[PDB]
Amino acid sequence: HKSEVAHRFKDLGEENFKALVLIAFAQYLQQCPFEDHVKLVNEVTEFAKTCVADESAENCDKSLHTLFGDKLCTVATLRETYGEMADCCAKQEPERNECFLQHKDDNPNLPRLVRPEVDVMCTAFHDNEETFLKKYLYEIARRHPYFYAPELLFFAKRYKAAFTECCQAADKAACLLPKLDELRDEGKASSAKQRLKCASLQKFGERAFKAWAVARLSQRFPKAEFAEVSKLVTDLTKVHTECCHGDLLECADDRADLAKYICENQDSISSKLKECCEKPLLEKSHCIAEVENDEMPADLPSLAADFVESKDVCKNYAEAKDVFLGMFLYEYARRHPDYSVVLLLRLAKTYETTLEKCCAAADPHECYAKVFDEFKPLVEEPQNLIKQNCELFEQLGEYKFQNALLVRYTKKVPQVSTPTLVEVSRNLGKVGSKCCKHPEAKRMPCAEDYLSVVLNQLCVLHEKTPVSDRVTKCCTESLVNRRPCFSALEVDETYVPKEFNAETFTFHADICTLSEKERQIKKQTALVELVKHKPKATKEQLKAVMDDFAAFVEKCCKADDKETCFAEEGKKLVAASQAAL
Ligand SMILES: CCCCCCCCCCCCCCCC(=O)O
Ligand SMILES: CCCCCCCCCCCCCCCC(=O)O
Ligand SMILES: CCCCCCCCCCCCCCCC(=O)O
């Protein structure tokens, strides 16, 4: 263990080191040009090979934290470009690394990355493959300076995979665009989850996080003993607190540790793990954390012995409340992978709340014998909406369904921005497609999964530009109560309808040109605007107007002189709708 650079270069491989060095630098120095970092990276790599050859050589003894610092502080235009940051360089180390972390900018002012024409990509990718990929790695890096670097590195390679396949396929855009849309979407998702998880830790504190993890880890490793789960939860909770804080190496090394541990103690934890524990350093902890729920033990009791019918319960509770409730959750979670992490927390919070009454009451055993009764309705609420709504998505496909929701929520929260209403109805809709194709024993996690990100995205927009007290309530409640609070929203019976607008219901023959996506967005803005103009309108009345609009369109887009039909027939539609409503 002579040299941390040498170890990390041996550990990683040149090609990975190089990628990670690049992502590291790109995250701290977001206003420098790609070609500058190639210079850095290669300067570091060239250096890193010295030490691999002879860990005694100049500076090899130095700390990665110290060599990264020294590198940063030899950028000349550093005060010019960044200003405050430069002042960090005047600190001797331990603080200096902190000072660079402090003065990172999350969310700079940078132009949106344009996706080129398919053919430009494939061509460039052929012409010069590495410079193509790293360039774009450099661009996502600077735009997400707090994203775990090897996770990012993992996407680059799924990216490389998608070029390698489709730029040798006759119909390039037919292949590539969905693959890339998948990845766009799967990275915004990921890059939100991290922001949520960290924000959850600061606001709600370390306790609740452990609660969450226990439920989770127990769902995943049901054969493990509660102490093992506790060992895991604990270290895992360290890991999130350190990775949030933004130190790459602390986050990395901590994670590495945990992967060693899990694979060394493999038999104690999960059968479904051999696979992952084969994969090399970088992929290990990624893989572990993605992995399937292990199959549950056949020989499995009711909980009721240890948590209802035993005496010694109030003693066992009071002896250590958080550990006893831990045990409750461990036992309840591993019996139910088909529950949402959050569902299981509603059980524990409800349980908790009874013992607070019943251990302090005259007859404890009798104050609480009817408590798993209290769970019955808590488990059915999420189960029912799933059945109800996945039934409804079965009737009307993804699209007709999106419009069902678009009506639903526009009624509930009419004050929302119309685009905002369209995007979430659209996004929700998609969840329906994804999660409803699973069986019932597998739906409720999937949906928690998705809803949680949508529901957050929702609440960030709202944080920035507030529009509704009732929304604010949900976004400023526990991540446990979040989804129900939304489900609890009712039709806004206060709402004053919006002044009719001629232009809003005028359409032109340009929509017949537009892609089915493009069209649908046009149609769907209308439907909202319609809902916001005549909210007191019935589904029947609405399916009426919607069907007319639909015929109208397909009349003027199967007609000579399209433009003048849209002005004339549209004149009718509006008057005849204005009427019916
Ligand atoms: C001059 C030195 C600059 C810093 C070097 C770049 C940092 C790369 C090291 C990250 C190692 C990641 C370890 C994998 C842990 C995991 O499984 O996620
Ligand atoms: C290894 C011990 C883990 C500690 C387990 C904590 C048990 C608490 C379970 C109830 C859910 C807590 C959610 C936070 C919000 C609240 O209820 O106040
Ligand atoms: C920026 C703020 C936008 C807010 C959009 C308000 C619309 C509410 C959407 C909540 C969807 C959650 C799914 C709940 C399922 C249910 O209806 O029971």
Image (cartoon, rainbow, N blue to C red):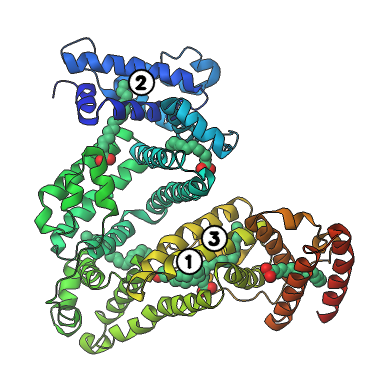
187 over 63 or under it: above or below: below
Q: Is residue 310 left or right of residue 483?
A: left
Distance from label 3 to label 2 (Cα)? Answer: 42 Å
- Nearer to us of marks 1 and 3 is 1
Going from N to C along the chain, the mark reached first, 2 or 1, is: 2
Q: What residue does disc 1 label?
A: 433
Observer-side mark, 3 or 2, equals 3
Task: Say which amino acid is labelled 2.
Answer: Gly
Expressed as whole percent of the image width and height from the top left, the position of residue 338 reads 31, 71
Residue 100 left/right relative to 407: left
Residue type of the residue flagged with mark 1:
Ser
Asked which quadrant contains residue 397, the reply is bottom right
Q: Position of residue 49 (x, y in %)?
A: 24, 16
**Residue identifier under label 2:** 69
Q: In what element is the residue under mark 3?
A: helix
Q: State the SS at label 1.
A: helix
In this rendering, does residue 386 appear at all? yes
Quadrant of the image occupied by residue 448: bottom left
Counting from the top left corner in percent of width and height, residue 276 is at 21, 49
